[PDB]
Image (cartoon, grey):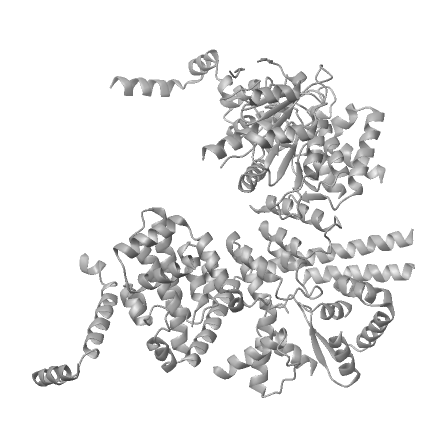
Amino acid sequence: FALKPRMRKIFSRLIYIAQSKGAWILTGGTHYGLMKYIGEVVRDNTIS
Amino acid sequence: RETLKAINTSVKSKIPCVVVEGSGQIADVIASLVTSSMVKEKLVRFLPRTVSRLPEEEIESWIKWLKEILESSHLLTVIKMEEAGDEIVSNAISYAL
Amino acid sequence: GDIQFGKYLRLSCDTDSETLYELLTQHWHLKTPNLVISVTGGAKNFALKPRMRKIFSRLIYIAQSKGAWILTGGTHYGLMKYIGEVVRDNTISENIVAIGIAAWGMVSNRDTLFSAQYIMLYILDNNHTHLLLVDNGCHGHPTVEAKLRNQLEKYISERTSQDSNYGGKIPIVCFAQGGGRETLKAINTSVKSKIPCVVVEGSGQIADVIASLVTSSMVKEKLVRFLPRTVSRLPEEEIESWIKWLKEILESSHLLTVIKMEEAGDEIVSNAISYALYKAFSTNEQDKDNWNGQLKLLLEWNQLDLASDEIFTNDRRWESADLQEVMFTALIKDRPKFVRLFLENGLNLQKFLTNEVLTELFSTHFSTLVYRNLQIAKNSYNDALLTFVWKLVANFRRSTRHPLQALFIWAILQNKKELSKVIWEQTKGCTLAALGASKLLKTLAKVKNDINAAGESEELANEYETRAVELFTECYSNDEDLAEQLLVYSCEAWGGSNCLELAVEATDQHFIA
Amino acid sequence: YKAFSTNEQDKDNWNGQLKLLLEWNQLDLASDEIFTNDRRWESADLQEVMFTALIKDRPKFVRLFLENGLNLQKFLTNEVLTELFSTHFSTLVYRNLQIAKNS
Amino acid sequence: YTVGIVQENNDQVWKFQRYFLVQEYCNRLNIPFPFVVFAYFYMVVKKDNETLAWEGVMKENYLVKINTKANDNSEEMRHRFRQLDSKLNDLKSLLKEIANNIK
Amino acid sequence: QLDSKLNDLKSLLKEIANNIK
Amino acid sequence: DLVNFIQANFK
């Protein structure tokens, strides 16, 4: 998985939108590549 | 590959959703597409090593899946790579729905 | 005949390339890590266009940096003369080899020969360090040096290199911007070999022909357009041979690289050369499936965008264990962009910093001058942080842990800006680390003998303190209580002190205010 | 220029073309047309145009000639400098210099 | 003149000195002086991860802010225009191919 | 916008080619 | 030495 700045920004905005709407998020959840990043983001979101 | 299968089975249902013409290469294939020879050559361009490794029958199935996906475009939305706005993501989702 | 003011010699075409290479390597010349041969017409007509001057100056700088040899006509006419001047300038400001190849029969003044000295068609140039004359046959001065130069280049391409990192082979790159016929012949005979190299769509007109081409009628009309007088003068059969040579050259394009005239960047030259070699390393098929060596080559030459485009992407599935070897080399090579790329492409920095890795790095890559300066500062001035840093560096030199802080300190003490920022972006205590870096740089500059290095260190410390101030302003604006908790947070063996103590001890009025 | 070149009376001529392009302040066209690799002008031909450019006050052409291979050091001969100073030093400037030196 | 010059850099130095004084008073027994002596007798008788993670999040936000400020030049549009030109060129090539098909 | 217009022309040409075939 | 080797190689 490549953490390109554009992809990181896009997925951070996606997580923010999901938080605002209260939407559920479904993912592979195996801690590899993109999924791992997603987890980190949500962690950050709950720490803020 | 499983991403392509998931996209196909989702589009078969009334599930509008989005692809991005960015790092994802099969997503780039779908965005560029939005004939069998053209889809094949696009896939080879974006998957030289991957297309070389795959067998003939499974890759014919790949082409069938991709054509079936490309059949319906209203449910299929794409994010332009040129766009750099901060609120682009939302837009896409919104438009899709 | 040997002349000094360098080594000169008269050779015979029957001379073996291996013997000449052994002679050159044994005593005078060091092993070549790369070669550049400049293909230019020997005619006295040469235009010193600013673009061409800049390009060739950058080429000479690249050759100096790599230590590459340079082969040229060396007759003191047109481009060659300019090249000599440039190299002279470079040595007035290591050493660069500027071998020149000419024909004994095409020399006006002959002074047969401790060392005979001669001061004065096509009289050889004196700026070149070494010069080789070959007129074993054709005493009337026809073209004979080209064959020997081609043979020597062919032999070099076959030679193995222990630490080249180009697959064990020397990159041979024929840089050509000449409009002459012999330039075309040299380009053709070079391309017939596995010699990737470059042309520029600039002043050179046959180079423009090749670039524009990259049918017989089209090549003919392009040649006539760029050589009206030249094409008119030439006979029919020789010009048909010209067209045949040009078609043969244009047959293969992977070895052929071109420089766009629109491009005006300062680092364009390098790129071209780099790309050329890259293609020959990849399209050669000897290591086309190879993955590591490609990345090592792209790391050697400062080519980041191409590496991201080609090496990475989803298909390869490189995995993590392969990136450690290139990360370690990038640390020494001072390639911060590649360090960031590797870090953001999945490399786990925390696992990478092993005790043995840090020990070896500190032992065999800490500047001796910097080590002496740090020792003097610790023994003379001393401080709450100098003692800690000195103890850590001595421990790693002789033989939680916070390895990230150690790497950040190592980067800081060598005065590496981009690398230090990249490492800082990974640490946990960012604000405290920035304050400590500013304090350490200030203290070191307080005991630094160098004049300009002191200014550089002061500027870096100012940058880091401004960074810390801005970070803390944002952090406090986000929240008022957690920011103060961070302020009072006691260092877990960073320096034993928190942000306030470091700021006050460093006299950082801006942060406190 | 075209009528001087395409006329075919002196189309093969090289010097006169450069003299004409030097008279009228046309530098870019001269670089494009007169120079380039095919002609092989050589050094001895550029001295006559450099001398005229010095008087004509055409600095761009002076720079062009200097960067196109002319050897300035050899160009400045004792006779050249003597004639130049004698028959091109402004009389007003000469009188002013004399007055300043004497006073 | 001196007062006019050194005014901007005076309040900052005073704030630094204020930190020094406040820490001196806080790092103290905080007892009224006329009785503080008793303490000197009595005393001589006897003689984290959450914050760091939050700081890291804010640091990421700050880096993002710097990068966005750098990218705010808004010149990328020009680049896009250039890309558009290339696209147009592509069309031309297609037309050429069509002509090759027609022939 | 002008660029887009130019692109439109290209498409028309393509259509013309489709008519020619 | 070096000159001797040079002339021997070059005959």
Q: Residue furthest top?
A: D79
Image quadrant in which you'd find residue C27: top right
Residue at point 48%, 72% (across, down): E61
**Residue C335 locus on image (x, y percent):** 53, 54
Horizontal side, residue C200 vs residue C238: left or right: left
**Quadrant of res E80:** bottom right
Report the front residue among B81 and C444. C444
Q: Quadrant of the N terminus of chain F?
A: bottom right
* The furthest residue to the left: E34
* Quadrant in the rendering for residue C26: top right
The residue under the point 24% across, 68% down is E16
Residue C492 at x, y percent in the picture: 37, 73
C452 in relation to B8, above or below: above
Residue at 71% x, 76% y is B77
- Please tell me which residue lies in front, C129 or E91: C129
Please state the total of marks drawn on the protein image.
Answer: 0
Percent across and percent down for residue C95 are 51, 35
The residue drawn where x is 35% and y is 77% is C489
As drawn, E51 above or below E86? below
